[PDB]
Image: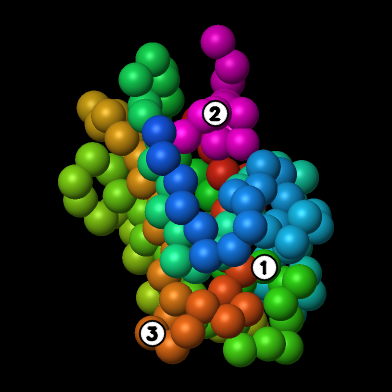
Amino acid sequence: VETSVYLSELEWKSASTGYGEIQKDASCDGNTITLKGENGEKVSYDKGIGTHAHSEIVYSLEGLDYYDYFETFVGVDQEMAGTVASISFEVYLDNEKVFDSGLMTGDTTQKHVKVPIAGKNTLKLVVKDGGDSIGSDHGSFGDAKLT
Ligand SMILES: [Ca+2]
């Protein structure tokens, strides 16, 4: 088995997005995924999932009970720096929310997610539209993986 498994290596049970394709290892516009770093500069990610509010992406963890955590960084993909981008990220394990970023705009520093998955069957990623419109709502999951 792999020591970690990127979500981009897995097939989802279902996936919706507000634009285009859910992109494997790229932003929803097909660029290298970038998030806002603590120093104000971009942080680039080789692996991850790029999507667009409103998005719900559901993965089965059947045959993946090997792993302790789901880990990822989340934020507005910095291809939309300077825009009206406004989103939130939620992560569910089975039927409960385990992570909620609250509102993130283009300048909001990326957030790290590390949630335990032991004993759970289903991982669901949600990108919501910040309560305005989906305009510029490009949300990326940097380094998203089971580990
Ligand atoms: Ca929005």
Residue beneath the point at 43% across and 81% down: 130
- Please give the residue where the numbered disc 2 appears in the rendered image: 10
Left or right: 80, with 10 as reference point? right
Q: Earlier in the sequence, mark 2 or mark 3?
A: 2
| Residue 70 seen anywhere in this rendered image of the structure | yes
Is disc 3's CB within 8 Å of ligand 1?
yes
x, y percent for residue 20: 63, 57
Residue beneath the point at 51% across and 78% down: 134
Q: Amino acid at mark 1?
A: Asp
Q: Nearer the viewer, residue 117 or 13?
A: 13
Q: Nearer the viewer, residue 20 or 68?
A: 20
Q: Nearer the viewer, residue 31 or 66?
A: 31
x, y percent for residue 113: 46, 54
Q: Are marks 2 and 3 in contact (CB under 8 Å)?
A: no
Callout in the foreground (3, 1): 3
Extent of the magenta region? 1-12
What coloring was used for the rendering? rainbow
